[PDB]
Every structure is written in structure tokens, then in C-alpha cells.
Amino acid sequence: TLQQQIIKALGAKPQINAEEEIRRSVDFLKSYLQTYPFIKSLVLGISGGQDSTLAGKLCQMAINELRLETGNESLQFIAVRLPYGVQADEQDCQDAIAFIQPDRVLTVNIKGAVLASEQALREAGIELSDFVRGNEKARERMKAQYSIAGMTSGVVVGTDHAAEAITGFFTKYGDGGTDINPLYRLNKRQGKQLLAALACPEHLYKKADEVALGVTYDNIDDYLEGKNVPQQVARTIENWYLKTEHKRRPPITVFDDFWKK
Amino acid sequence: TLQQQIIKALGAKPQINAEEEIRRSVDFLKSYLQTYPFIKSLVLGISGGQDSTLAGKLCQMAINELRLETGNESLQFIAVRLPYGVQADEQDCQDAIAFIQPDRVLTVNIKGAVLASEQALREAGIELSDFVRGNEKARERMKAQYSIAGMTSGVVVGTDHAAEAITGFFTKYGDGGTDINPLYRLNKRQGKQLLAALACPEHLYKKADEVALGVTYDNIDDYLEGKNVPQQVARTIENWYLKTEHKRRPPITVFDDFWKK
Ligand SMILES: Nc1ncnc2c1ncn2[C@@H]1O[C@H](COP(=O)(O)O)[C@@H](O)[C@H]1O
Ligand SMILES: Nc1ncnc2c1ncn2[C@@H]1O[C@H](COP(=O)(O)O)[C@@H](O)[C@H]1O
Ligand SMILES: Nc1ncnc2c1ncn2[C@@H]1O[C@H](COP(=O)(O)O)[C@@H](O)[C@H]1O
Ligand SMILES: Nc1ncnc2c1ncn2[C@@H]1O[C@H](COP(=O)(O)O)[C@@H](O)[C@H]1O
Ligand SMILES: [Mg+2]
Ligand SMILES: [Mg+2]
Ligand SMILES: [Mg+2]
Ligand SMILES: [Mg+2]
């Protein structure tokens, strides 16, 4: 079935072992850095939400272990705060930072750049809708992170996971534009499982997308776990998947044929 | 050999038929638009250089033919000028536009946005090198094009081809961040062949990268055509290819193993 094919493509499992998955992600990050020794930093945008809090903790753990094992003091995890003006859940971001205990935290306000981009487009004749402005913000955040990685010999860590990949619920070349994604394979509730195992404060992942999707995260997680969900729900999820295949593949060329089916 | 594997992966051929390749690219663009009818525009940044001039002409031809065939007057090709302040070869851009005869030309000056992004980074403690600033400009151009595509129901056309893909000579999520690439498979001199067949003014592609690469475009084209080049030259090209595999694949996950070889 299509459900079977999607589960296989995203690497999702019905149940996972929290600590075992924590080690799988940490060891992954450590192995990559030992294979490419010129990389001295891991860069990640912290939003105060579940996914970035989890990824952030895993990144710091990876660097902490590599330092002790190799003695290389130049390695570091750089957490990046990218507020648009004044961010609402700022206190949550502070709590997330306290939990992660990052080596370094840089704060870059993207408002000025976004307004400038919009002014240039307006003068040319293009006014943006709120939806498009949202993607523009996601792309400015990508830009900031890559400029930081470029000056610190680092790579940009992404928070993409199975529950977001299946619906293509990310901005193309926005938060989707990253170098390495240690959470890929996990669904939403499983991410909470890892945070619980890390003793993360409950309020940082205890409830917050479901509006635009037409399905809840529980529907998506159940689907990814191979469960039997209402047919109408399955069709909605599958429609999103097929519609967004372009977001999970490199630019289309004359050799591609996936879009012909 | 590695040369054989690379040629296969990029789809390059020793010799091509100019008109036949022109039709292959145009028919490709037309087929995609007929498969996804919600797409009403093709968006492409025009720089006055060889690659964008070629891609631009092919895009306009595709739209011209689709309009006559379907009668749909809402379809259009949008050429986008994205100068950083005052562009040097501006006259060449004007000549390129005269050759392409685009339905619409929008001019968006990216200088304001780039300076704003740099100011935000500077205040946080990050000063950019000229190289990194260059990538930042490429990413702001990507941002502008996607905002335009978002408001015009369009897709972003890329100019990536075999001679650039082999060395990864493009900005990750910059000019490399596109939706559909009609030139993919062609080497540099072959691109000139297509322009000659289209009667493009010679000065628009007659000579202009080779500095940073350590090899000339003729070395790269010869390599892609399966020719026997000096071993030192082959090793340099192959080094670039292996080093930039991350640019030609989606973000790295725990399931990938290409980087382990
Ligand atoms: N306010 C923010 N500050 C820093 N990073 C952000 C911000 N908002 C989004 N991000 C990053 O974008 C990722 C994707 O967010 P989301 O769009 O909610 O899936 C998060 O995991 C963060 O890494
Ligand atoms: N079917 C498609 N094939 C290739 N690119 C597309 C397609 N549908 C949408 N896009 C591109 O993806 C963008 C929407 O992605 P996002 O900005 O992430 O919401 C549109 O502005 C187009 O540039
Ligand atoms: N000045 C510019 N104006 C508009 N598009 C640009 C500009 N410079 C670069 N581009 C776009 O980026 C692509 C890649 O350029 P290149 O970095 O020279 O390989 C070109 O084919 C254009 O589509
Ligand atoms: N070996 C690698 N694996 C994954 N990402 C990398 C690697 N080498 C470089 N990068 C990323 O790609 C960027 C360089 O690409 P560019 O900006 O196109 O010159 C660096 O700033 C890193 O974010
Ligand atoms: Mg969020
Ligand atoms: Mg998220
Ligand atoms: Mg150029
Ligand atoms: Mg080019």
C-alpha cells in the first residue's frame, strides 16, 4: 500500500527505544565530525519549540563527548536565536537554552532584512501575502545560519522529522535548507519520548499546523506507525505527500520521471 | 573509472545535436506545465551571462508555444533582474533581454537587503568575508525569486548544467536552490552550441571561475566528453566532485552512507 511505501521512504517505526535513538543521533553527529575534521561547529536555530529543543540538546551532547574524547577545544555548538522583532514565547526560548546549556548563543534579529526585501519587491510591483511573507522569514533564517556556518567552519543542523516530511510542512530552501538532519525518521510523539528521557521540562514540549493540514498530529503519527486510520484521513495525508514530493528531492531535470506518475 | 561514473551521474554526452537538445528542453518545460496546470509562470533571474541567457530563451519559447497551443493567455515568462547596487555589465543584460523578448521583466535591487542582513550579523559579532558575502548575495537572489513565484503561481527555473554540477560551483540553497533545471546534462561549450543555433549575439557568450577551480572550462568540458586529459587535471576535477557531493543531494540523515566512502 501507499502507507507502506511512505513509511519505508521516511524510515518510520511503530515504536522506538528512546535512549537507543538518542545514542543513534548523537553517534551520527560525532561520526560525521570525525570524518570531516575541518568542521569545528554545529549551527542550529533555536525557536523554543519541541523539535529545535531536542535537536539542540543532541548537538551539545555530541560536541561535549567529542571534546572529551579528542581533547579538541575548538569544537563548539552554536545556538542561534532568530527573532522577528520581539518573539512572543521568548521566555520559553530562555528555558530551552537553560536546558541545552549551549557553548555559545548568538541572537540575530531578522526583521530589518525581511522589511528591506519586502520594500525592494514592493517597488518592483510585488506585494506579499502573509503566507509568502512567512516563507520569506524562514529563508532569511536559513541565510543567517549559513553565513554563521561560513565564518565558523560549521554545518547547519536541521530539525526535519517524519511527521513534517510526510506532509512537506516546511519551507523549501527555508527551514528545509540544512546540511544534516539528526531527527529524520522520528514522528511527533516519539520526539516527545526522547525529550522525556532527557528530563526536558514538560512545558517545553507539552502541546503547542493542524489547522492548515486538515489532520491532527495524532492522525499523522498513527499513520506513520502503520496503524489503521479512517480512510478519509489516510487520503488527506497521502494527498499532501504526493503534492510535496518536489520538496524532498533535488531540482527536477529532464531525467526525472516521478512527476509523470 | 570515476570519470565514467561521473559522466553517467550527470548525463553528459561526447557530442550533442543543438536543435534536438533545444527541443528536448522546451518540450520538458511544456510537459511539466501541462502536468501541473496551476503553474502560470516561469521565473528566472537574468544576469547577462551565457547560462541565464540560454535558459531564458528556452523558457520564453516554451511559454510562447503553450499559449498558442492551449489558448491560455494567463501563462507568462518572468525575467528577473537582480542587481547588487549598479551592475557592471548592465548593457549586456539589456542585449540579453532584447534577444529573449520576455513577457515581463521585474528589477529588484538586492543591495538594501544584503546590507541589512550584514548589519544584523555584525551586531551579533559576525563579520563576513568577501567569499561568504558572495554566497549571501546568491541566497538573497533565491529569496527574491521564490517570493515572486509565490505571488505569481510560478516555479523557479535554474541554470545548473554539467560543467557547474561536476565541481559544485554554485551556492548551496543560493543559485542552486531552484525548482526545475532545463540545462542539466549539457557542458559549457555545448551551451554555446545551443546559443549559436538560436542566433544569439556572439558577445553574449563569447568568453567571460577558472581561477578558483585550478582547471579551465575546456579541461572540464573535455573531461565530461570522456576525453583523455592529463592525470593531474583529472585528479583535480575528481577532488572537487567528491568534496561537493553534499551539494547535489538532500540533507544528510542517519540512513545515508555515501559520505562514509
Ligand atoms: N524564532 C526562531 N528562532 C530561531 N530558529 C527558528 C525560529 N523559528 C523557526 N526556527 C527554526 O526553524 C525550524 C523549523 O521550524 P518549524 O517551521 O516550526 O518547523 C525550527 O526547528 C528552528 O530550527
Ligand atoms: N509541483 C511543483 N514542482 C516544482 N516546484 C514547485 C511545485 N509546486 C510548488 N513548487 C515551488 O515551491 C514553492 C512552494 O514551496 P514553499 O515556499 O515551501 O511553500 C512555489 O513558490 C514554487 O516555487
Ligand atoms: N546579477 C544577477 N541578476 C539576476 N540573476 C542573477 C544574477 N547573478 C546571478 N544570477 C542568477 O544565478 C545563476 C547562477 O549564476 P552563476 O553564479 O554565475 O553560476 C544565473 O544563471 C542567474 O540565473
Ligand atoms: N562536507 C559537508 N557536509 C555537509 N555540509 C557541508 C559540508 N561542507 C560544507 N557544507 C555546508 O555547505 C556550505 C558551503 O557551501 P556554499 O555556501 O555553497 O559555498 C558550508 O557553510 C556548510 O554549511
Ligand atoms: Mg515552531
Ligand atoms: Mg518544527
Ligand atoms: Mg555569472
Ligand atoms: Mg552560470
Image (cartoon, coloured by chain):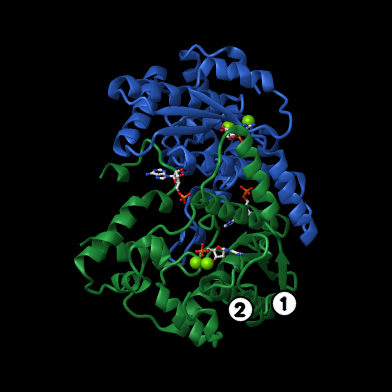
Chain colours: A blue, B green
Image quadrant for the N terminus of chain A?
top left
Residue B153 or residue B236, whichever sits in front: B236
Q: Are marks 1 and 2 on the same chain?
A: yes
At a point 34% along the width and 34% down the height, the residue shown is A33
Say what secondary structure mark 1 lies in.
loop
Q: Which residue lies under the disc numbered 1?
A: B71
What is the three-letter code of the residue carrying label 2?
Answer: Met
Say what secondary structure mark 2 lies in.
helix
Residue B12 - label: none
Where's residue B182, x and y in %?
50, 68
The subunit carrying tag 1 is B
Q: Is residue A197 above or below residue A241?
A: above
> Is A61 positioned to the left or the right of A242 in the image?
left
> Looking at the image, is mark 1 or mark 2 earlier in the sequence?
2
Residue B247 shows up from this direction: yes
Where's residue B51, x and y in %?
51, 71
- Tag count: 2
At a point 34% along the width and 23% down the height, the residue shown is A67
Residue B57 or residue B229, whichever sits in front: B229
Q: Which residue lies under the disc numbered 2?
A: B61
Residue A169 shows up from this direction: no
Residue B233 or residue A15, whichever sits in front: B233
> Is A109 positioned to the left or the right of B197 in the image?
right
- Does the CB distance between marks 1 and 2 fall below 8 Å? no
What is the three-letter code of the residue carrying label 1?
Answer: Gly
In front: mark 1 or mark 2? 2
At a point 60% along the width and 44% down the height, the residue shown is A171
